[PDB]
Amino acid sequence: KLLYTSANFLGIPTNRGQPKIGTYQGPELIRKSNFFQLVAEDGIQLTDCGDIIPVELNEAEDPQRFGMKWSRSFSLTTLRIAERVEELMKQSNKSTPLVIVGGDHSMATGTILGHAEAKPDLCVLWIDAHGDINTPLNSASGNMHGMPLSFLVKELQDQIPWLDDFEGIKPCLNASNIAYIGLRDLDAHETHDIRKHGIAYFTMLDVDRMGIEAVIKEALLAVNPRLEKAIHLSFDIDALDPLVAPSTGTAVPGGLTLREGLRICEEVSATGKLSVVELAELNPLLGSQEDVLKTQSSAVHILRACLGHCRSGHLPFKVRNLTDQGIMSRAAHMQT
Amino acid sequence: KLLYTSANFLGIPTNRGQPKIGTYQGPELIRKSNFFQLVAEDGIQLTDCGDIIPVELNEAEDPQRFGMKWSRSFSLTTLRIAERVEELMKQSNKSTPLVIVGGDHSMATGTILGHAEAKPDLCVLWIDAHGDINTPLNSASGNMHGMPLSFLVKELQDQIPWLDDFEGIKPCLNASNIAYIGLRDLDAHETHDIRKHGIAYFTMLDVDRMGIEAVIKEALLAVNPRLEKAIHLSFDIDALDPLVAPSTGTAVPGGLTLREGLRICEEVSATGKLSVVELAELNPLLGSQEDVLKTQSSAVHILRACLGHCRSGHLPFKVRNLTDQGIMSRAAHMQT
Amino acid sequence: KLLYTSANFLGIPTNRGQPKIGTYQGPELIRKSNFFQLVAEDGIQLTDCGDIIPVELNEAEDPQRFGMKWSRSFSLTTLRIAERVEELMKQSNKSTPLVIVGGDHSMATGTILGHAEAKPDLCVLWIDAHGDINTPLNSASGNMHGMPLSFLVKELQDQIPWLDDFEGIKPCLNASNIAYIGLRDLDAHETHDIRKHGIAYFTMLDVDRMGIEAVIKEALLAVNPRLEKAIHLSFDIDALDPLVAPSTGTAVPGGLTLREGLRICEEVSATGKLSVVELAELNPLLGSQEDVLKTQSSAVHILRACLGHCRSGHLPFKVRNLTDQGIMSRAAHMQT
Ligand SMILES: [Mn+2]
Ligand SMILES: [Mn+2]
Ligand SMILES: [Mn+2]
Ligand SMILES: [Mn+2]
Ligand SMILES: [Mn+2]
Ligand SMILES: [Mn+2]
C-alpha cells in the first residue's frame, strides 16, 4: 500500500549560482525539521546519503566569462553532482526516489545530467516562478541559477557560447521532455525560446483559468502521456507564494498556494514514476525567524507529498484492540 | 427576512483538554470584539448566557488513567456542560441557535451530549484539521481535546476503556450522523476508524479536487439529506489556514481559506437547521498581538456567518428619505 | 503586439475624504517603486503628468454640512480633478490609458466627472470591498470617500441634499453603467439603493460561487456587452485581501487574492477599452514596513496588469544571436 517504501536523501548546498548567501544552509534547514521523523511514521525508510561538496573557486581562478559569474565553479560542481547522482540512481536500478535539497537552482544542471545518465528517457517537471533557461549572453545578472536548463536543452545549443570546461556537460534534454508549472516572471528571451522550441509551459495565468487539476494533467500529458518515463521533479520553492515561502532569494507575488503545490507533488508521486525530486532556493538567512519557519514548514509538507504522504490519511500497520491488554471496554462492561 | 431573530451566546473556557494555557481566554477574546454589536446591527437579538465554569481538579485528584490527562476533570466538566446546554436548548424548544465559544475542543463531548438530549436526531458537522476521534489507548499525548468524538460514537465503544465516572457520558451519536470537513492531519488509527465505520469525511484533498461548494453539498447530503435534522456545527478554528488563524494550539498549514470557512457557515446557516454552533481552540496567548487580532477577526466573521450575516448585503429595516426632514434634494432643486 | 503603447501617469494625493493621515503619500509610494522601469521594459511609454493639488480648506471655511466632513474641500477638489482629467483625456483624443494613483477614493467623483466629459458613454468597473455609494444623510461617518458614486448616479439625486458648491458636479452616470466586483461590507442603505436601481454587483459570495472568470465576464457583459464603451476602472486597494494589501484604511478580511485582482485587470486591459484606471486608498503610514512593501508590491503588479503586462510572458523586441558578436557556440564547435 506504498508506491515507494525506500528513499534516498541528498543535500547540495550550492550558493555560487546566485549572490545572496544562505542557500548553502538549505539542507540543514530540512535536516533539523521533523521531516525524517514524519517520513518514518509513514512507513518509508529514508537513507540520508549526506551532502555533495560544491566546488567553490576564488575570484582569481574563476573570473567572468561571457558575463557569467562563477562559471568554472559551476562546471566543476555540475560534473561532481552528476557523478554522485548517477551513482545513487544506478545503485537503486518498487523504485527508490532520490530526494535532493538545495542549494540554489544551479544544481539542476548536474542533477539532471546525472539522473539522465541512469535514466536517459526521463521527463522534467519544472515547478518555478522563473524559466531558469536564460542563455549566457541574454542573462542580465550572469547568475548561474537563472541558466541551469539552457545547458541541458539540445535545441538551445546554438545560443550557448562554447567553453572547454563545459564539454562534459552534454545536453541531455529535448525541448519536448520539459514542462513548466507556476511561471510568472519570464525574461523576454526565455519567452522567445520556450515558444520557439515548443516547450510545454503553464503559467499562473493558466493555473487561474484552467485550475491546478487540469494544469497538472495537461503537463503530465505533454511530457509523459502514458507514464512510461521516469520523472525528474525540479521544485523551486519560489514557485509557492511568498506568503507561504518568504525565505527565498527571488520571491514573486501571486504564486502557487501550498495546497496547489501539494496537488502537483501528490499527482506526480501517485504516477509511480517519481525518480528524483529536488527542492531548490531555500535561504534561511532571508526574512524573519517566523519567515524561515513558514518556508521550512512548506518545504516539509511539499517533500512529504512527493514521497507519497496522503492528506486523506494512512491506515495503521497494526490495528490495536483493548482485549489484548486485558482491558475492559465500555461495550464489554454494558454487556455484563 | 431572517431565519434566526434570536440567539444565545455561551462561553466554555476549557483548558484541561490540552497542555497550552490560554484557550480559557477564548470567550473573552470574542466578548471584547465587536461581535455583539455587529450581530445587533443585523437585526438579531443576542443574549449572553454567561460562562460554564469547567471542573479543574488538582494532580492528586486526577492522575493519569489509560494514558489520559485530566480525565476526571473531563468527565465532570462534560456532565456540567451537558446539563447547561440541555437546559438552554429546551428553554428554546423561528429556532434560537446556541453560539458557544471555547475553550479547547474537549468541550464538544459535553456540548453534543447536552444538545442531543434536547434534540436526539441531530447531525454533526465537524470542521477541523483533525479527526478528534482518538480512542484513549491510541492517543499519543493523552490530551482530551483529541478524543471528544470517541466517547460519543456508538460504534467505537468496544475501543473505549470503561470508567465509572464516564457512565453518564452516554454515546449518543451514530457514525452515520457525522461529517468531517477540512481534515489534513489524521492519526493512522483515526483513519482506520473513520473508514471502517463509514463516517463521512472530506479532507483538504477533497476540497482541492471537488471545490468547497460540492464538499458542503455532499457533507449535508451525507448526514442531513432533506434538512430534517437539527445541525450541530462544531468548528475548530485550526480548520482555517494559519495565515488567517495563527493563534491556536495545533496549527496545520494548507487549511481552509476564510472565504471557504465562510461558505460552510453560510450554507449551514441557510438550511434553517443550525441548532448549535461552537467555535473551539482560540488561544489569545499564542502568537503575536497581530496574530491574535487576525484570529479574533476570523472568528467574528465565521460566527456572524453562522447567525445569517450575508456578504451580499442586508436590506435596511426602515428606508429613509430627504423630504421627511424638510430637506431640499438636488432633484427637487432642479425641478424648480 | 501591444494594445497600448503610450500611457499617462497622474497622482491625486486626496486625504480629506477619510480621517486617517497618509493616503496623500500614495502616489509617492508608487513613484518610488520600480513601476515606471517595469512598464518601460514592457515597451510602453509612460509619461508622468505630475500631481493634482487637492483643495484643503481649514475648519472655519469647511464646517459640517448634512453630516459631511470636508464637503467644500471635496467639491472644490472634485472640480479641479475633473478639469485636469478632462484635459488629459482630450489631448489623447491606439488609445492612451490614464493611470491615476490616489489618494483616498473620494477622488473618483472628480475623476469620473472629468473622464465622462471627454467620453460620455463610458462604463465604470468598481473594484472595492465597499459600495462607496452612501448618500450624505445615510453615512454613519460623514467621510467623503464613502460617498463618491452617490453624486455621480442620476437615479440617486432625490437622496442627495442640494448644495450650491455642488452644482458643477453634474451626475453623469446611469445605474446601468456601473458594475461592482469584490463587495463584502455593504451598509444596509447601499444594499437598498444598489438592488432598487438595478446596479450590477458581484460580491465575494459571487466570486466564491461563480469563480472570478465568470464574474469578470458577467460584469463586462452587464455594462459593456460588445466592448463599445470606454472603461473606467476604479480599483480600491482594499478590494484585495489584507494579507496582500494591509496598508489601507478600511481593510476587510476575505478579499480578492492578488491573482484574482490580476485577472480582473488583465481582462479589462485586453478589451482594448481601458481608458482610465485609478488605484485608491494606499496608505503607507499604516501597518509595518513589510506591510507597506506588500501593499506597494500588489499595487505595482495590479497597475502593470492594467497596462497590458502578461504573466505568460512577452516576446523580445530584438532577438539576439551569437554569430553577430563573433562568438563560437557549442553547436558551432561540435560541427567542426
Ligand atoms: Mn525561481
Ligand atoms: Mn529556479
Ligand atoms: Mn484541530
Ligand atoms: Mn479539534
Ligand atoms: Mn473600500
Ligand atoms: Mn473605496
Image (tube, coloured by chain):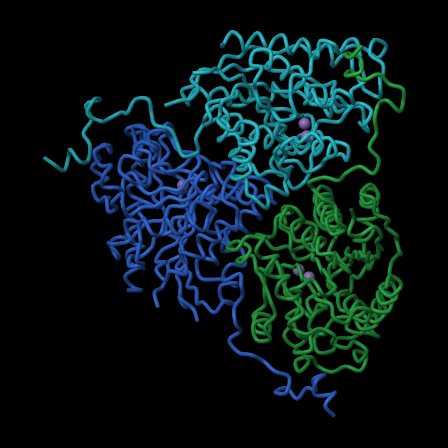
Chain colours: A cyan, B blue, C green
Q: Nearer the viewer, residue C243 or A72?
A: A72
Q: Nearer the viewer, residue B147 or C83?
A: C83
Q: Residue furthest left?
A: A336
Dividing the picture into quadrants, the one containing residue A145 is top right
Tell me if I can see residue A335 in this picture: yes
Q: Residue furthest front?
A: C335
Q: Is residue A238 above or below residue A4?
A: below
Q: Residue at x 37, y 62 (%)?
A: B272
Left or right: B206 as drawn, with respect to C210: left
Q: Residue at x 27, y 43 (%)?
A: B175
- Quadrant of ligand 5: it is bottom right
Could you say where residue B275 lies in the image, as x and y percent from the top left? 34, 58
Tell me if I can see residue B81 in this picture: no
Left or right: A294 as drawn, with respect to C173: left
Could you say where residue C33 lies in the image, as x and y percent from the top left? 81, 44
Dividing the picture into quadrants, the one containing residue C214 is bottom right
Could you say where residue C130 lies in the image, as x and y percent from the top left? 63, 62
Could you say where residue A332 lies in the image, as x and y percent from the top left? 15, 33
Count of marks placed on residues: 0
Q: Nearer the viewer, residue C133 or B288?
A: C133
Dividing the picture into quadrants, the one containing residue C34 is top right
